[PDB]
Amino acid sequence: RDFNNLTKGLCTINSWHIYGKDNAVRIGEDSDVLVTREPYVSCDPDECRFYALSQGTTIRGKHSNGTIHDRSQYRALISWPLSSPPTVYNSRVECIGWSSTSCHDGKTRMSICISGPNNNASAVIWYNRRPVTEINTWARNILRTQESECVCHNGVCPVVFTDGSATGPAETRIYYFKEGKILKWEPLAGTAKHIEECSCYGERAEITCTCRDNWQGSNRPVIRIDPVAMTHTSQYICSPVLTDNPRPNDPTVGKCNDPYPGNNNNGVKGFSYLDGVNTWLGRTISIASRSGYEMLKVPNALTDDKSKPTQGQTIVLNTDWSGYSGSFMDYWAEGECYRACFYVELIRGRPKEDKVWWTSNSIVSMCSSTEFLGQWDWPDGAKIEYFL
Amino acid sequence: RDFNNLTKGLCTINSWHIYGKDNAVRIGEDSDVLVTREPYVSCDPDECRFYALSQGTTIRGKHSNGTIHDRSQYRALISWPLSSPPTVYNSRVECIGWSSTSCHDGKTRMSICISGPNNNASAVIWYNRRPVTEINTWARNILRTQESECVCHNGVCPVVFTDGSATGPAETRIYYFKEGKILKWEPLAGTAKHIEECSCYGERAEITCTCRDNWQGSNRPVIRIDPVAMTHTSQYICSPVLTDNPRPNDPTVGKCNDPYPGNNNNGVKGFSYLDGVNTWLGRTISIASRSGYEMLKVPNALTDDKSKPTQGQTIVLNTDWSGYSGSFMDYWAEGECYRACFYVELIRGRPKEDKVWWTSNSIVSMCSSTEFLGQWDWPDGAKIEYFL
Amino acid sequence: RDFNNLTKGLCTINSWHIYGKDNAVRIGEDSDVLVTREPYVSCDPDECRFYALSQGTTIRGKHSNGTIHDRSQYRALISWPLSSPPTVYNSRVECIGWSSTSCHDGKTRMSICISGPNNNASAVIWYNRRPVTEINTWARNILRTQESECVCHNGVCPVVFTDGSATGPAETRIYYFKEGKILKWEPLAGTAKHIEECSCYGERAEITCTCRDNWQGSNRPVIRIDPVAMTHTSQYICSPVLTDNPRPNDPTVGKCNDPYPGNNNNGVKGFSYLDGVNTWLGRTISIASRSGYEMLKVPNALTDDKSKPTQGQTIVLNTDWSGYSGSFMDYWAEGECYRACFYVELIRGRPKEDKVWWTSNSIVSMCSSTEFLGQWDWPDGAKIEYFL
Amino acid sequence: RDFNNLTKGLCTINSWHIYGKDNAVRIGEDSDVLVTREPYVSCDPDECRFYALSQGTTIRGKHSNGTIHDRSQYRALISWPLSSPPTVYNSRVECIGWSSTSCHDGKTRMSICISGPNNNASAVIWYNRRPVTEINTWARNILRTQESECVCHNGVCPVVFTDGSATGPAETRIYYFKEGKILKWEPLAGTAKHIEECSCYGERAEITCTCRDNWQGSNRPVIRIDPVAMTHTSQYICSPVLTDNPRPNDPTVGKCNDPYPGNNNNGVKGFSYLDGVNTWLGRTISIASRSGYEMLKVPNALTDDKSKPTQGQTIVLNTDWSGYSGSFMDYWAEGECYRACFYVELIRGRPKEDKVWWTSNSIVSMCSSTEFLGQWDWPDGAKIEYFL
Ligand SMILES: *[C@@H]1O[C@H](CO)[C@@H](O[C@@H]2O[C@H](CO)[C@@H](O[C@@H]3O[C@H](CO)[C@@H](O)[C@H](O[C@H]4O[C@H](CO)[C@@H](O)[C@H](O)[C@@H]4O[C@H]4O[C@H](CO)[C@@H](O)[C@H](O)[C@@H]4O[C@H]4O[C@H](CO)[C@@H](O)[C@H](O)[C@@H]4O)[C@@H]3O)[C@H](O)[C@H]2NC(C)=O)[C@H](O)[C@H]1NC(C)=O
Ligand SMILES: *[C@@H]1O[C@H](CO)[C@@H](O[C@@H]2O[C@H](CO)[C@@H](O[C@@H]3O[C@H](CO)[C@@H](O)[C@H](O[C@H]4O[C@H](CO)[C@@H](O)[C@H](O)[C@@H]4O[C@H]4O[C@H](CO)[C@@H](O)[C@H](O)[C@@H]4O[C@H]4O[C@H](CO)[C@@H](O)[C@H](O)[C@@H]4O)[C@@H]3O)[C@H](O)[C@H]2NC(C)=O)[C@H](O)[C@H]1NC(C)=O
Ligand SMILES: *[C@@H]1O[C@H](CO)[C@@H](O[C@@H]2O[C@H](CO)[C@@H](O[C@@H]3O[C@H](CO)[C@@H](O)[C@H](O[C@H]4O[C@H](CO)[C@@H](O)[C@H](O)[C@@H]4O[C@H]4O[C@H](CO)[C@@H](O)[C@H](O)[C@@H]4O[C@H]4O[C@H](CO)[C@@H](O)[C@H](O)[C@@H]4O)[C@@H]3O)[C@H](O)[C@H]2NC(C)=O)[C@H](O)[C@H]1NC(C)=O
Ligand SMILES: *[C@@H]1O[C@H](CO)[C@@H](O[C@@H]2O[C@H](CO)[C@@H](O[C@@H]3O[C@H](CO)[C@@H](O)[C@H](O[C@H]4O[C@H](CO)[C@@H](O)[C@H](O)[C@@H]4O[C@H]4O[C@H](CO)[C@@H](O)[C@H](O)[C@@H]4O[C@H]4O[C@H](CO)[C@@H](O)[C@H](O)[C@@H]4O)[C@@H]3O)[C@H](O)[C@H]2NC(C)=O)[C@H](O)[C@H]1NC(C)=O
Ligand SMILES: CCCN(CCc1ccccc1)C(=O)[C@@H]1OC(C(=O)O)=C[C@H](N)[C@H]1NC(C)=O
Ligand SMILES: CCCN(CCc1ccccc1)C(=O)[C@@H]1OC(C(=O)O)=C[C@H](N)[C@H]1NC(C)=O
Ligand SMILES: CCCN(CCc1ccccc1)C(=O)[C@@H]1OC(C(=O)O)=C[C@H](N)[C@H]1NC(C)=O
Ligand SMILES: CCCN(CCc1ccccc1)C(=O)[C@@H]1OC(C(=O)O)=C[C@H](N)[C@H]1NC(C)=O
Ligand SMILES: *[C@@H]1O[C@H](CO)[C@@H](O)[C@H](O)[C@H]1NC(C)=O
Ligand SMILES: *[C@@H]1O[C@H](CO)[C@@H](O)[C@H](O)[C@H]1NC(C)=O
Ligand SMILES: *[C@@H]1O[C@H](CO)[C@@H](O)[C@H](O)[C@H]1NC(C)=O
Ligand SMILES: *[C@@H]1O[C@H](CO)[C@@H](O)[C@H](O)[C@H]1NC(C)=O
Ligand SMILES: *[C@@H]1O[C@H](CO)[C@@H](O)[C@H](O)[C@H]1NC(C)=O
Ligand SMILES: *[C@@H]1O[C@H](CO)[C@@H](O)[C@H](O)[C@H]1NC(C)=O
Ligand SMILES: [Ca+2]
Ligand SMILES: [Ca+2]
Ligand SMILES: [Ca+2]
Ligand SMILES: [Ca+2]
């Protein structure tokens, strides 16, 4: 009908309830399930769907061998019904590529896939299921994007891309699209030193993205975007509760405008909801590997450099594998406020479970409740020995 | 369009005709069929569908091992087209959980799934395919619900939950929802001593639920609900024709307000249509196990403590397995009265058939006819030796 | 929109062109294809579909063993997209039973399935996908129907049933339904001595059915029905070109009102288009088994007892298996006249091919052309040795 | 809504971006994928789909043995969602045949399939999914057509057929259809000596087809059609950059009205976009086999007999297999001009890869960009050793 506008604020998050779970690897042990990674969730005005980058083979298929590799010509952004597994028969291909983002602006959906050699990649923006705009690599070193949904406001959907080194200063740009066309683009501003895989959400006409400093920070960079003025700024989450992975142990005081040193050249896509006292951070439990997952209420994490948790909820136990995590919200749900949601990628196979030759994942997603619900852990559930 | 109102009374039930049957286990022997249990049937204004709690694996899949277990993080309420089997590719996930109920109010469908640890479970009410309300456990001992459809009247859909001991007094509540929000809730009233898995239907602005006293009764408790006044009362079916399982042999006189003693701490979800002389009870043929299934016309069973059958129809022979059974009706069918219907879960595998390591089921459902149709038996049809 | 009326006459049939073919057995050798038999084709105002009675198992599945049996509780009328195979995932169940018919009246579709023991069978009429009317067996000996589509005119859809002996006089009735309700029923009139599996079509407000005299006739009985007056009459096709199977060799002169003697207690469902000089009969090539299939133009076959073919077209070579065949037409196609169509069931497995333990079929269907198209043969195409 | 009119001209083609890729053979190694060949892509006003001629068996199925054969009764034109593989469950059959073309005129789609013995083949034209017109063979030697989409203008959709010798003069006709009926047909005019498998596109009320001279030309014939006047003319592409296969090495000067001699009785379906300086030719890299694929910008190739490439883009490396290629465009995309697109069939199996007994393909398709995008190669991706 009409372009969606971010007119509400977030609901109070007192706990998280189970939203969707696909049990993809359990089911894929004996069904035609596609090998995937880098999944996310994204809603249209009438339906919410699971998304991920397919590897172009089933798990049980012989071509699953080698799916630890990130970029190839056999990957594609696919979407499928909520809580179903990504099967060969119920999956819709959005575009061809090895990096992506996608969002509905209220009228229709824009999907962006990037493909190519490391030094000659290109992004093709699809709108209403047709290619509309194409952007060629500007730094010649793996043009890449969010790996989770973008957000729009009155037709304008900002998207964060990064081109260049994964372990040094790189060239990050914020593009502002409207109906698939580029309205404008900015170079990154503010104090964030490196940006990768931003996880975004919007409320009260402002867009907040929590990204990943793959270079030196263990605290996460944040990009606040103004989709009307088409401007932005960046900094790091101030809290000592560190959310990247691998990372050092939490200190007593964090940093607001500099990376917190400790681990270099590594990380994991993550997110956060930054809303004053209504602030919740997500992180792996393990400081060493992508293992376990918990949500921690850390009042004013963004600005208070000594903020510590006042409440929490375990999502995945530290004995189970986790992986990427990002934000999304059903901006079209009935109600007075936006209900915050998130997904966690549960990676199985290589590199941790080396008995199999593949790497794939299942998904678990939750949404906030104003109630204080009891907690449960939500692991992948597959038994690797069944695949040997 | 508009909220459905229970304006008709039941049609005369002179016999039962075959409505739907999925042959899930026969077909699943060589197709990607999901392992399920606790199925039911539920209609929308334009289509009737099969529902059940998936175990998150196919029957032939290696993860089918162990599906005798009731609660895990891999279960989900799924729905699929009438008479089709629950396959990985044609199944729609309604919500994540190990206990459920669902009903269409005329405008849209409300689905409720409960998940969690035994001591910290929670129910999340979905309406129009979005989470709306969440209720946390109140007795800390397996919050659970109907396992068959709820019923609505003018927007109000009562749902019966039980939290606490399965073998002692517990805390049962009747919630009255309208568009996913709680309008009110009551503690159980009347003489029923224990309530579990209520099977409900509605006619002439009143809702009747036949439940299961898992503690001491072999006669079944009934809850009559008034969805306008939002009040209810309870008692037991008076008839000596006992319908729980396991149960003692039928006596010559039954009890109206007390459990009929004999078997303790066990039972099976069942139902009945209580309509004066137009009364039919369903029960397993075996008094010892969930074996066989028959419908018996027992005039005034609800109130006459010496009522005995005047007619009957065998649905499943006593040599074949049965299981749960519940009521539903297509409240949107053309016609002068509501046609009573029911389904029977045909459980295969553990515990009775221990040669396989899984537990699953198929479904058979019938609806009433005003004609006196000839009868046939409707067993599952799968040959277990084919799975060894 | 509105009830369809048979306002046109048939187009001139100068040859037959390929309409649809599913290659079900070839494909089912390595796909989840359902075992079927007794197929047919039937159109709705916006789509034409393949129909058949499923055996409730896939071909490669272990339960395929024994599917030579006609009646069981695992059969169901299913429909699926034109030229696709009947797979577990793309098949829609219409009703449960081992004998059926179905037709669209212009507003919606009526489907009828019969199920039960041989002596207590019953038909349940579904209209707009809901059960509406039920008819119990009247002769207590396998109540059965057409096995191909019925035809409607202004809301009224006559259906021919037979109850009683398959090899003696039986009780055949013509029911006239309108919106699933019985308007009236007649006992068979005219000179036909036995009626089974009628194949019907309609033109210029009249319905013609070519059936099967399983008792003594090798010439086929015809029932002409007047759907407005709700009356009918019957006779046999006069031509010496015999179309039942097994049958004697063609004589020089046929019979109009008596069965042509020769083979007793056997036959095959077949059809014909009887339209003066525009008359075409279908028959197996073999007089001994269901082998081969050809269409022969026999001017005035219905009334001329010495009529012989003036043109023909081979559909299936005599070295390939055939089986049932029936008529249907897309009454909603654009055009000045109705294009005659037909399907042939290509049976594979038992009894002829005894190396496998199953019996199933694929379908080939053609429609008339006013052109004189070249011919090709259309066999099933599967290699039985691949299933051993 | 209304008939589509070719009112725009082509967009400037500065490079090609990835549009769709199905990875059919990789996926089919462990999924129910149909064996195909002769694929193409074609759009409707609201969706673009992949098309191909199925062989009526899956790749892993035993009937895949022998699919190197072109014509049989088990082939059918099928369509399926863009970038999905042609699976048994997501594929829609358009018509039965071993040669085809299809196009949407703006209101609905016309599909044409040809089937039959070599000497008695016939084409049946379907419009709005119903058979409408039938054409019988005129030269009695494999009546055949485009193998890629046709194009329409104001209701009129010309289609090029060829009947007769594949290695001598034959009888080629251009039929002009409107709503499935023949408005008129012409014998081929101009200087083209032989025509096979034309690849067409339209812009500014004119239709251009690049075909294949299977007899003596290594330069390609072009047919320009005027869909309003219903007339046409033909010639050869003048450029020395030869695009058929197998072919001689490029000379310094080409021929405009005669076949360029060198290879006889062979070729491959190909295409080109002829638009003055905005001209791009597609060709296999290898001059000997269907190996590799590249696009070359050759300004004024159609008329300049010494034109050579000024830019290029490799699509498939010469170490990977290619095959047929053709044109299509989404005539319903938003925008000021038509974006040129094309697909390449990536053939795997026989005859080149003789270790397997089947022949099948996957598809890669690209569309033009006004940007100068970096390039990547897009091979099939399957490992044949996995099928042994
Ligand atoms: C029924 O359900 C309810 C609702 O869920 C249950 O109640 C909830 O119970 C939760 C579990 O206790 C509770 O969460 C906890 O909340 C406290 C604040 O009150 C919070 O501090 C906890 O978080 C710390 O603890 C967990 C491990 O327990 C850590 O994994 C987490 O990271 C937090 O500690 C780490 O960081 C802190 C800040 O930097 C450090 O001070 C601390 O030392 C620790 O650091 C080490 O570990 C880090 C992680 O590996 C590492 O990075 C660092 O370097 C150090 O090595 C936790 O969130 C909920 O608040 C509570 N909710 C409610 C409403 O009550 C109830 O139990 C259930 N009922 C039953 C019968 O079970
Ligand atoms: C064509 O189709 C028609 C239509 O279906 C057929 O006609 C129908 O035939 C039915 C079968 O005879 C008939 O049903 C019976 O109806 C009578 C009342 O008329 C009813 O009493 C029967 O029910 C008792 O019998 C069955 C076993 O036969 C029991 O399983 C059932 O539970 C009932 O008995 C038990 O409970 C009674 C009440 O408490 C006790 O008095 C009795 O002893 C027995 O108790 C023991 O068994 C219990 C069950 O295990 C146990 O819990 C208890 O502790 C005791 O151990 C049955 O419903 C239909 O009424 C009739 N319908 C019509 C319209 O006529 C016809 O046969 C078919 N035609 C052909 C040729 O076959
Ligand atoms: C390109 O395509 C065109 C178009 O299709 C081809 O032209 C067509 O060619 C057809 C084949 O010749 C031709 O069909 C024949 O038409 C004649 C009438 O003109 C018709 O009589 C033929 O039918 C008899 O013959 C076939 C076997 O050839 C039998 O199977 C059939 O049943 C008919 O014979 C049987 O019944 C008769 C009547 O009772 C008996 O007189 C006769 O003896 C025979 O009886 C025995 O066999 C019976 C069957 O088993 C059995 O029941 C009985 O007891 C006896 O044992 C046939 O239909 C088309 O008319 C013609 N169409 C056109 C427009 O020309 C052309 O060849 C193709 N081009 C090329 C190069 O091939
Ligand atoms: C990032 O991406 C960009 C964008 O793609 C890259 O830049 C592009 O790089 C392309 C590759 O160099 C370049 O394409 C080439 O363009 C030139 C014109 O400038 C064109 O001549 C090239 O085509 C010839 O060369 C290829 C092999 O290189 C041949 O396969 C092709 O057929 C052409 O040569 C053949 O035909 C000619 C004409 O007849 C003959 O003169 C020539 O000898 C040759 O003939 C033989 O081979 C034939 C084929 O087998 C055979 O039939 C014949 O008989 C003879 O045996 C090629 O298209 C793009 O123009 C350029 N694009 C842009 C915008 O710059 C950049 O490299 C990437 N960045 C990085 C870091 O890699
Ligand atoms: C830092 C995150 C993105 N990068 C670095 C890409 C890069 C490598 C080398 C040089 C420059 C850039 C990653 O490797 C991501 O890592 C991970 C990962 O699990 O950490 C998976 C992503 N599939 C991958 N992204 C891409 C495009 O390959
Ligand atoms: C009495 C019916 C519900 N209960 C008891 C739950 C309970 C156990 C122990 C203590 C308290 C409560 C059951 O076990 C039901 O039994 C059966 C059953 O077949 O009898 C299957 C149901 N899947 C299960 N329900 C749940 C939630 O697990
Ligand atoms: C004559 C056609 C219908 N009959 C006879 C049914 C009957 C048997 C014995 C006594 C009375 C009636 C058939 O056997 C048909 O035969 C055949 C067949 O291939 O000849 C298949 C049909 N599936 C079957 N119909 C039914 C209902 O079983
Ligand atoms: C020249 C292209 C079409 N022909 C020649 C048909 C023909 C043969 C012999 C005599 C006359 C005509 C082809 O063989 C095409 O070749 C090829 C091919 O890969 O070259 C595949 C096509 N499936 C096939 N077309 C048909 C209809 O069979
Ligand atoms: C969003 O705001 C714009 C004007 O700023 C308005 O035209 C549009 O309809 C609004 N969207 C909705 C969904 O109301
Ligand atoms: C149900 O009754 C309410 C008023 O009590 C009415 O507004 C509604 O339309 C009724 N529903 C239908 C389906 O008529
Ligand atoms: C069929 O005829 C009836 C009246 O006899 C008419 O009301 C109906 O609309 C007609 N059907 C169509 C499709 O015109
Ligand atoms: C099929 O069943 C029969 C009888 O039930 C048995 O002897 C036969 O061996 C079975 N065939 C196969 C392949 O299992
Ligand atoms: C195409 O042109 C015809 C008239 O020449 C017109 O009637 C039709 O609507 C046009 N099509 C569109 C899509 O405008
Ligand atoms: C395929 O068929 C040929 C000839 O029909 C046969 O020799 C060959 O072995 C078959 N190949 C396989 C793998 O079955
Ligand atoms: Ca980091
Ligand atoms: Ca009990
Ligand atoms: Ca006979
Ligand atoms: Ca050539």
Image (cartoon, coloured by chain):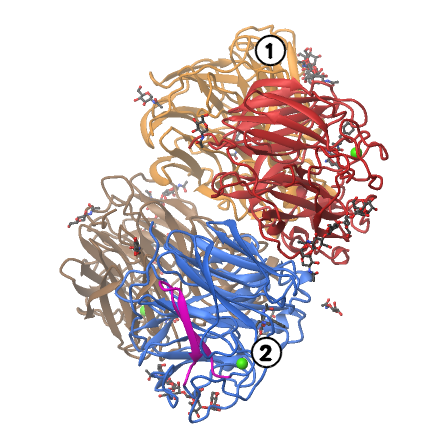
Chain colours: A orange, B red, C blue, D brown
The residue carrying pointer 2 sits among few (fewer than 14), some (14 to 19) or many (20 or more) residues within 10 Å by Cα, namely some
Judging by the rendered image, the residue that carries numbered circle 2 is: C168
Residue A30 placement, left or right of A152: right
Alpha carbon distance from label 1 to label 2: 87 Å
Q: Quadrant of the N terminus of chain A?
A: top left
Amino acid type at mark 1: Val
In the picture as drawn, the residue positioned furthest to the right comes out as: B262
> Which residue sits furthest left?
D229
Residue B385 visible in the picture: yes
The numbered mark 2 sits on a residue in which chain?
C
Closer-to-camera residue (C385/D342): C385
Q: Residues within 10 Å of mark 1 (few under 14, many from 20)?
A: many
Which sits in the foreground, D128 or A70?
Answer: D128
In magenta stretch: residue C229: yes
Indicate the amino acid at tag 2: Gly
Task: State which region is magenta.
Answer: C218-238
Residue at mark 1: C-beta within 8 A of ligand 1? no
Task: Using the rendered view, name the quadrant where residue D70 is placed.
Answer: bottom left
The circle drawn on residue A298 is 1
